[PDB]
Image (cartoon, rainbow over all chains, first blue to last red):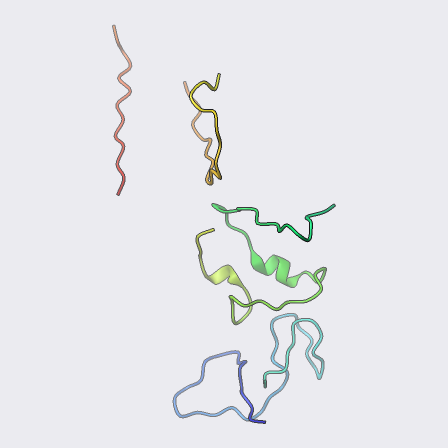
Length: 44
Length: 49
Length: 34
């Protein structure tokens, strides 16, 4: 299925891209390969 | 103790300022499926009641 | 007493602030709703 980048720390600049996804952090602190509590996968 | 399952808790709390991030940071709750705020918390917006 | 009123709706925004003190005192008040 097609994918969406529905999580970013900042806003996208015009004619830019974001291909590298490293567990979007909601603000807990640790998100190294873990979706625990705050951290969620940016791609849905 | 209780709030009933057939009835609902619709307490009208308003005219106050509180930090939603205070409850967000606490891990006592089970899960977060918030619909209002996109990024993290409601502390950047104001509402009615 | 409370002879003024007998019922009570969902009154929101309850407020209690002011500590109180010839004709002398005037007690001039202006109520404006804008």
